[PDB]
Length: 375
Ligand SMILES: CNCCCN1c2ccccc2CCc2ccc(Cl)cc21
Image (cartoon, rainbow, N blue to C red; front, side, top):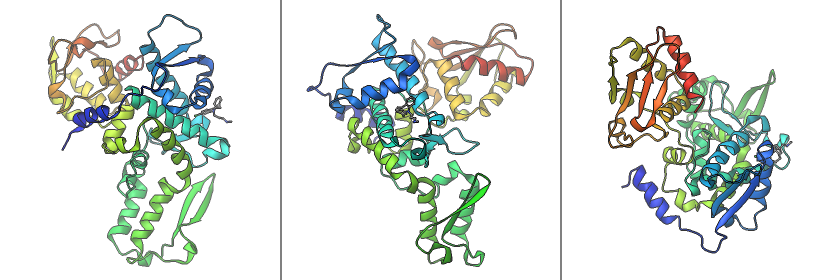
């Protein structure tokens, strides 16, 4: 079979170029109104295929800028807007998570929400098509729905561990005596909302004969049932740019990396293939604090730290042992530089972090985090 890199090459090979299209897609936008201007342009095109031409984007009448750079900025800005839970289309999957899911009540907020989701799908599609990234991390069932993969009990673990553990107990033990019914109780606005999982659900006892169905219905309720039209609209837009059959060569981890550049960073592998300069070593107090910091950063923050030091967010295949710098093989590097007063600096050409010898973990935490959020 093919690993991720070979799959991606294969994928691009099949993604043929449109010839029956204008040679560029022109889009003039104002920053104060990027979302509305982008929506009007991208949903107004005569043919979705027009969006496959070279992006020719202009902000606030600013002429004389590299159209390649402007596009990348646009994908960033439009992501921030589209995925902002304030608009009510997406929401965080849990109070303690940073991953996004489709808001079941998206329609209450926005009568025209299906066209907004189709638009979001078109833009996601445009990112994949033009080799750019969306800035946003979705829950794993989002990616699976895109790929028409079944949502499973396991998917519930990454999103809600308490719930996952309860359904798993149900799967492994006879639940009959608990006298559970085919209903779901959701806590909202200081009240309990009960929903029947099937007709007459309240009077149907969960047992070993029907618990596989119970679990299926609970999972569909949590991730699918209430957001079918929304996701259908997103997929419609997405598939106007990327043939659905082509996207199927990827699994859900590969797809997420493809679209959003996010994934789980093996800090162990990162750690073992780091080099040290000018006094630093694996056992050095400051270094011990560095790895302590990295270990307690979110996957998002780990990625962005990697981005800061290397210049890119991509984690090399076969791990950090094969990381490249600017002039050949160059391991991730931490060098002692500067006094504790200044922030850490990055030499991207050498994948090198210049790290002052801070005198406290919390100071290191503060200084390192400050440096990253500028990138
Ligand atoms: C009240 N409805 C809000 C609609 C959200 N929306 C916005 C946001 C700001 C300004 C205009 C609009 C309408 C167009 C639009 C288009 C796409 C998306 Cl994703 C959200 C929105």
